[PDB]
Structure formats: structure tokens, C-alpha cells
Amino acid sequence: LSLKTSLSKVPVNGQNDAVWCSWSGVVCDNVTAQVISLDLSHRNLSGRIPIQIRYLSSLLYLNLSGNSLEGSFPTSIFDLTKLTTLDISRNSFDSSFPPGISKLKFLKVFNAFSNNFEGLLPSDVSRLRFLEELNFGGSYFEGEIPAAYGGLQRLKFIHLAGNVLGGKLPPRLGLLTELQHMEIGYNHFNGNIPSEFALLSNLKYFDVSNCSLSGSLPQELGNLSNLETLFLFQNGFTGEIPESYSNLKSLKLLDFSSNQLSGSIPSGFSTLKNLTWLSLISNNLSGEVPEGIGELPELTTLFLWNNNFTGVLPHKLGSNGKLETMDVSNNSFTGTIPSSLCHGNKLYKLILFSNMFEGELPKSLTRCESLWRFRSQNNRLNGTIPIGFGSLRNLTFVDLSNNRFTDQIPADFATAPVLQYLNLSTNFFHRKLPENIWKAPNLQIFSASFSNLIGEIPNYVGCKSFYRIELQGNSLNGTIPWDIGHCEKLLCLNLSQNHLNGIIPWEISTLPSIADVDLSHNLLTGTIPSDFGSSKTITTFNVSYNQLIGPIPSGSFAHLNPSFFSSNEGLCGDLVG
Ligand SMILES: *[C@@H]1O[C@H](CO)[C@@H](O)[C@H](O)[C@H]1NC(C)=O
Ligand SMILES: *[C@@H]1O[C@H](CO)[C@@H](O)[C@H](O)[C@H]1NC(C)=O
Ligand SMILES: *[C@@H]1O[C@H](CO)[C@@H](O)[C@H](O)[C@H]1NC(C)=O
Ligand SMILES: *[C@@H]1O[C@H](CO)[C@@H](O)[C@H](O)[C@H]1NC(C)=O
Ligand SMILES: *[C@@H]1O[C@H](CO)[C@@H](O)[C@H](O)[C@H]1NC(C)=O
């Protein structure tokens, strides 16, 4: 009986983003006892609730959410005694929440999420003993959780996240026999999680993250079966993960990231067969990862980075065919990379950098049809980078730098359809560049620096998307290709520390956006083409330690660092000619 359906020659036009108190005011004028539901949500309304609203004495349902209602909460609403659900969420109500909610003794649902309330949580609420859902999150509430809130049985949902609450969590809250959902993180709570919370047998969702809590993780919480979501991240928990937590048979999501947990991932975790998401990022965890974690049938997300895990990755990880994102960077992992990681073609993000992984890149990875971002720099991977990556049609980011790869660079990389980043630096190839590397349709950053490259730099035909090129610190001999002007997007070029002889390619002056150029430590000869001096993008031009000849250009080279030169010949920039 809302939206102006039942009248209740009078308008029932609910739109035209009008402010309010009298756009309705009228809508309560209709003395009506035939109005049981009032849904004025999302009408861009603004103003106050008028006192006259008390005459809708038959109201059961009132939704005023998603407007711009302001001022203190309207006490008049409390005179709506048959109110059963009340939604005032997503508004701009401020000041302390006034006492008097008690008269709404039939209230089952109170949602006031996202408002401007301040002061203390109303202790008043604890006398609504039909109440089931309570949402007071997203405001500026202060102080402690009133221990009397634990007197709310039938209550199955409580949300108080995103306030400025603090103190210690009231152990009495554990008496909430029917609580299924508890979301009270993003506050300033301190102290430990109460042992008593282990009595919340019906609890399916447990937050309390981004707080200031501490202590060991309370073992007793292993009693909380039925629990599907356990978020305790961004706190200050210490000690080990309790082995009792392997009894959480319903657990789907686990997040202990950004704490100070130590010890090992308990081997019982291998029995949590419903785990979807396991995140233990940025802790002081150690020891090995239980083999059984690679056989969890539903595991899709695996975050273990910034710990100090040792040992092998579980042989059969990924064999469930459901692994999507894995990040175990910043550890001390060893052994080979399991071949089963991308079984099912669901793996799209594979981040393994900063470990001690050895052996050959498993060739199965080249048939990972969903792979999108691959970062495995800083390891001990050996052998030849396998051929097949260029056939992955969504591979966009590859970092295999600082490894121990040898012989040839796979020629498919050149024909990878969407590859945007490719490093490969620091790697001991002792082979030529693939001769059609610069035809890569998409490739913005290519950095095979200090990778023991040899031979001539192939002709820059194509060079469509390149804007950063790093090939410094190799043994590239021959001449810098004279067709470098095909690289119209180029910004930074480093060919320093090679064996490049011959002239500086004039066609560099043709580049619209070239900014940083380093050709230092080579065997270059000839002039710096004076047309360089009319560039209005070149910021760095290090060409020092060469055999160049003639005057340095003027124009926009007159304000360059003289250090950029160290060949026998110059102009006023240092020693006149
Ligand atoms: C209030 O309205 C919004 C959108 O109109 C809806 O999603 C929400 O469930 C409503 N609240 C209640 C308690 O029914
Ligand atoms: C993770 O690496 C960061 C720097 O990348 C470092 O500050 C931190 O100490 C590392 N943590 C562990 C547990 O190795
Ligand atoms: C991590 O463990 C390995 C040896 O198992 C070693 O790097 C060191 O003991 C630990 N590193 C840090 C930073 O604690
Ligand atoms: C390529 O990798 C090296 C070492 O792994 C790193 O120092 C460098 O910054 C990387 N280059 C780019 C462009 O990311
Ligand atoms: C340098 O280039 C010449 C081309 O004549 C080639 O014969 C020689 O092997 C190259 N140097 C190497 C590969 O070390």
C-alpha cells in the first residue's frame, strides 16, 4: 500500500526530485488507517520527517533508504507501534540516536546502515526481543558495544562495521543463540576475541577485520561449525593458527592477512574440503605448506605472499581444475613448479616471484589458455623458456627476469596477441634476439637487459606499441638499425653497455615523443645529428663513453647534462671547437 497506489482529484505523482516535508506531509494528511506499507526509497528526497507521520498508526513496513534525509532521527517514528521493519539506511541522519525505540516492540528488522550518527550506540535496542536484523554500520558511532545487546535472542544478523567503536568485545555477545551473521569490523576494538563466541553455534559469517584486536587466536572457535566466512585480517593477532580450526567443515572463505601470526599452516586445513579462498598474506608464517592443500576440491584462490614458507609447493596443486588466482610471492619456496596448476583452464593470475623455485618452466604452462598475468622474476628457474606462450590469447603480462634461463628466447613471444609487458632481464641466454620481436602487435614494455644477448639488433619494422625498451648490458654487436623511427610511441630507450658501432640513427630525431635515450658505453662513431637539437621531448641523452665526433647540437641540447658526453670532441657545453 505504498508508492501512492491506493489513494488512501488528489496527486499520487511520486517523482520530480522534490525536497520534502510537504511533498508528502500530504501523504500523511490522508488520515488513513488503510496504509500498511510506505516505501519512499530512492526518490532523491531531502528534508525532515514531519511530526504528523505518527497518524500512520497501522504502518508495518517503512523504507526511507537511499535518500538525503537529514537532521536528528525523528522521534515521531517511534509512535508507529505496529512497525515490524524499519529501513533508514543510506541517509544523512546525524547527532546521537535518541532513546525510545522500545515502543516498537514488534520490530524485527532495523537497518540504519550508512548514516551520520555519532555518540553511543543506543542501549535502548536491547529491549526489542523480537528483533532479528540489526544494522548500525557505516556511521560515526563511538564507545563500546553495550553488553546488553547480547540479550537480543531471535537476533540473527548484526552489522556495526565502519564506525569509530572501540574497547573490548563484550563476551556476553556469545549468548546470541541464533546469530548467523556478525559483521563488526572496521572499528577500533582492542583486546582478544572472547572465548564465549564459541557458543554461537548458528554463526555462518564472522568478520571483525581492520580493527585493533590482539592476542592469540582463541582455540575454542574451532567449535564454530556452520561457519562459512572467517575474516580476521588487518588486526594484530599473534601466536599460531589453532589446529582446532580444522574442524570448521563449512568454511568457504578464510582471511588472516595482515596480522602477526607465526608457526605453520596446520595440516588439518587439508580436511576443510569446502575452502574456496585461503588468504594468509603478510604474516610471519613459516614451515611447509601441507601437501593436502593441493587436493582441496574447491580451492580457487590461494594467497600466501609475504611470509617465510619453506619447502616444496604441493605436487597436485591445481588438479581440482578450479584454481583461478595464486600468489605466493616473497617466500622461500623451493622445488619445481607443479604442472597441474592450470588444469581446467581457470588460472588467470599466477604470481610466484621472489622465491627459490628451481627447474624448468613446466611446458603445461604454455597450454594454460586462461593465463593473463604471469610474474615469476627472482627465482632459480633453468633451461630453455618453453615455446607456446604466444598461442595464449589473453596473456598480457610476463616477468621471467632474474632467473637462470638459457639458450634461445622463444620466438612465439613476438606473436603473442595481447602481450603488453615482457621483461626477461638478467638471464644468461647467449643467443640472438628473435628476429621479429619488434613486430609484436601489442607490447609496451620490453626489457631483456643484462641477459647475455648477442648479435645484431633486428630491424625496427612495425614497432607499433613499444614505449619502453631496455637492452642494456649485453654483447649486441653491429649497428643500431636506421629505421628506429617506426617506433612512434617510444619514450625510453636504453642500449647502453653493448658493442654497438657505427652511427647514431638519424631517424631518432623523427620520433614524436622520445624522452630518455641511453647509448652510453658503446663503440659509436660520427656526429650527433644537429637535428636532435630541435627536439622538444628529449630529456636525457646519455651517449658518453663512445667514439663520437663533431659539435654537440644546440637548441634544446644546450640545457642537457654535460656528463652525457665523454668522447673526444665537443662544443661550448664543454670545451670550445
Ligand atoms: C528498502 O529498499 C531497498 C531498495 O528499494 C531494498 O533493497 C531493501 O531491501 C529495502 N529494505 C527492506 C528492509 O525491505
Ligand atoms: C615481504 O617483502 C617485503 C618487501 O617486498 C618486506 O618488507 C617484508 O619483510 C617481506 N616479508 C616476509 C615475511 O618475507
Ligand atoms: C626464512 O627461512 C629461511 C630458511 O628456512 C631463511 O631465509 C631465514 O631463516 C628466514 N628469513 C627471514 C627473513 O626470516
Ligand atoms: C625488469 O626486471 C629487472 C630485474 O628483474 C628490473 O630491475 C627492471 O626494473 C624490470 N624492468 C621493467 C621495465 O619492469
Ligand atoms: C658479431 O657480428 C658478426 C657479423 O659479421 C658475427 O660474425 C659475429 O659472430 C658476431 N659476434 C658474436 C656473435 O659474438
Image (cartoon, helix red, strand yellow):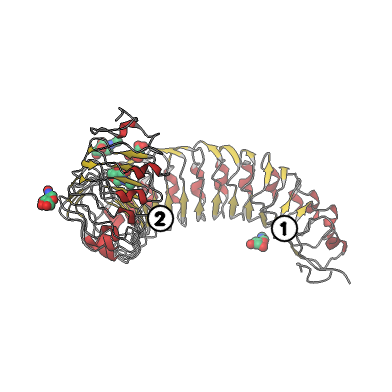
Q: Is residue 153 left or right of residue 34?
A: left
Q: How many marks?
A: 2
Please tell me whether mark 2 or mark 1 is closer to you in this view.
Answer: 1
Give the alpha-carbon distance from disc 2 to disc 1, as whole Å: 38 Å
Q: Is residue 89 left or right of residue 3?
A: left
Residue 369 placement (x, y as % from top left) = 31, 66
210, above or below 25, in the image: above
- Toward the top, the furthest residue is 575
- The residue closer to the viewer here, 555 or 320, is 555
Q: Are marks 2 and 1 in contact (CB under 8 Å)?
A: no
Instruction: Identify the image quadrant of residue 568.
Output: top left
- Residue 277 - label: 2
19, above or below 475, in the image: below
| Residue at left offset 50%, top offset 56% | 204
Is the CB atom of the residue marked by disc 2 within 8 angstroms of ligand 2's nearest atom? no
Residue 142 placement (x, y as % from top left) = 64, 38
Classify mark 2: helix, strand or loop. strand
- Residue 44 - label: 1
- The residue closer to the viewer here, 434 or 43, is 434
Classify mark 1: helix, strand or loop. loop
Q: Which amino acid does label 2 sit on?
A: Trp
Q: Which amino acid does label 1 sit on?
A: Asn
